[PDB]
Image 1 (cartoon, helix red, strand yellow):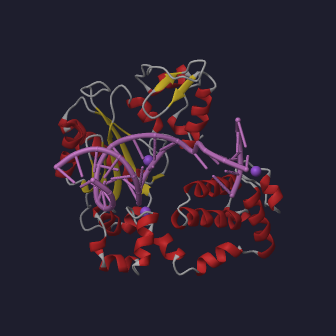
Image 2 (cartoon, chains in turn red, blue, orange, cyan):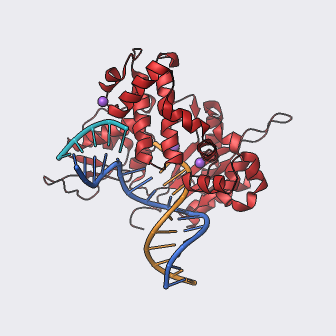
Image 3 (cartoon, helix red, strand yellow):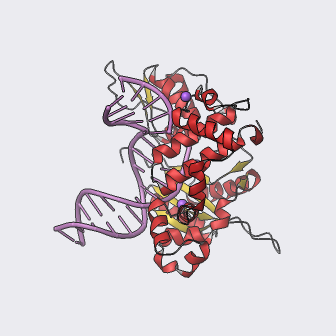
Length: 326
DNA sequence: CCGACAGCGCATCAGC
DNA sequence: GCTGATGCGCC
DNA sequence: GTCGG
Ligand code: NA
Ligand code: NA
Ligand code: NA
């Protein structure tokens, strides 16, 4: 429900996760805090003690104990000193720039660099990806309105076809799940001339999308995966639409739907499916669905021509993309 | 008590 | 020059 | 940090 119920607690947890991830470089601690913060979100009751929250999956002794200290004092000793930390705050912030992870953030903060302004003055100490992340700092933190997504979709699809009518292109993520807003645009690309058996295939797409002035920057590009920046055309005299993150993967036709399924998520939904496929005699990854032997041994890939085949194999009513949150 | 917690493509760097 | 390590993003 | 073996 609404934040107020356990916002103070979930906020603390989230703040702690960011600290562990950006500062401590302890990714598993980050996830442990995040998982607990989200499970405490679902909870329909005002948590009155740590022991209460402990009754949940993902909440152990340490978090239960911080919840006890939080309820009593309204603060968190640890988070307090962390907010004072002249370094922890700065390292946390810099990682908000795409291309700057825990390592670079720390190096910058040690060289005295700790604000966007500092970054602008020292563009020379940043690689190409980081320069772009700095350039579109604000634009990258904005949500993309579904209405805008559709508009972008029509552009990609249209252009993809303009190059070769046999190109299959699907847009996934929260978009393909119907959501009103999306963080970025993920596009899965395939072509009949590309399978797990058989360079200008992905390239001529990125190339074309550059010609119609959609894709504006490249973070990374190779023969199978592309990550860059796109933008919708300006409606005369009106604000130029913000720049957006676009990913374009070239997946083999024989593992395209497993791809399509995996990248449509949500990840929590996939887990409730991966773990279900596991106790029914099947394994689902990003590329293929495979049959297991008695001794947990895998086996050759099984023919998948549609996102539906995956469900039939593990006997699970084809869930709808519209209601596949979990 | 103790290990796993996902694993991969691209960019870039270290060691040679 | 190359090969392997590493940092980064990301269901 | 939490869970499972
Ligand atoms: Na618990
Ligand atoms: Na970042
Ligand atoms: Na995505």
